[PDB]
Amino acid sequence: TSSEQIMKTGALLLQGFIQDRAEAPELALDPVPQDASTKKLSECLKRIRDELDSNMELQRMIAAVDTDSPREVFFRVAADMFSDGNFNWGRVVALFYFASKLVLKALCTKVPELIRTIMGWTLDFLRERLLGWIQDQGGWDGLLSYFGTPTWQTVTIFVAGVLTASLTIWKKMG
Amino acid sequence: TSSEQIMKTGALLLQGFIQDRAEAPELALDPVPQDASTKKLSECLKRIRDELDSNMELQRMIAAVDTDSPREVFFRVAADMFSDGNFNWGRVVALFYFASKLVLKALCTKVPELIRTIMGWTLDFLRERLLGWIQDQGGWDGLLSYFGTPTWQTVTIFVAGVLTASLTIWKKMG
Image 1: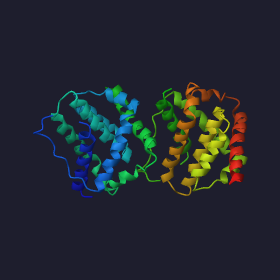
Image 2 (image 1 turned 30 degrees about the vertical axis):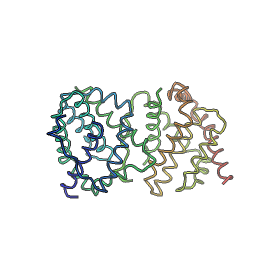
Image 3 (image 1 turned 60 degrees about the vertical axis):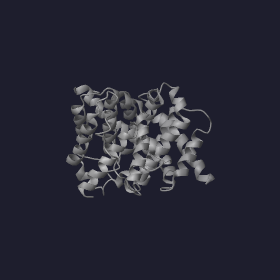
Image 4 (image 1 turned 90 degrees about the vertical axis):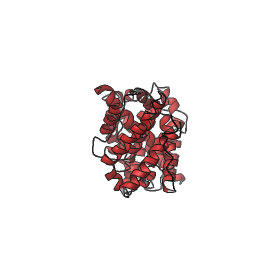
């Protein structure tokens, strides 16, 4: 519940979204030693991550993102997504899911320098805008509770609900 | 008219019945971005929802439901309500109205974990038993047609007619 701890687990999770699906090996980021706690979180998020991968309306919007000049697209999404001073785990999770495919959309266009670059922005944005609220949720473990074991496909609708809804605004305001 | 679309609008409407009247903010479900189409549906259902709120014979039966062990009461109602392989919008609407107050009857007994849980069951039941028929009605927009603008208080009688009639059977078969 020290920033450190939250930052730490944060990168770990973030990296989870990424390396699970897909590039100079010398600059690679050595996998972060998971333990029990962060095991169930990641075990969970990969379950979300595929229901989301399977949401087309989201996939469409995702497809509409600047595949290789995404500095601005990320920070404007992240801004709007919490533009209301509230926070739920849905929102956090989505931001993470979004960042993930930002990468996969760049790895495909083969610009691996940015793995780091994006992982940078997020965890930055984590610290600047969320470290507080998470700290005040007893840390990440709350996020498990956000996902009880039958209600997968339901929350996921609402969680894509917001992410789509925000990409969409970006899509029109330029 | 893809399941997605129908599922989507489905949650949106469902959530409409609920959050319009009334609880850990961290697990909250972020409101689903409405558009024009689903605007009139929800604009409509809230008009039904109050004529129903105002039907006492229904309110009585509603009062007789297990306030906090409702897994079975819901699925047995939903079963009987379409136990005849026919479908009208009245029936659908009522199922939705019922689920709504199931929640409000639980929020009052302060068990907010179940918001999700019930929203789960319904949209499940939506998919398994209704996605077909709605798909074959050109989707939800048909439901508007079920409610022409003078004949409010009439259909509502028949719509409560069925819902009461089904709770009633549950009330006796145990």
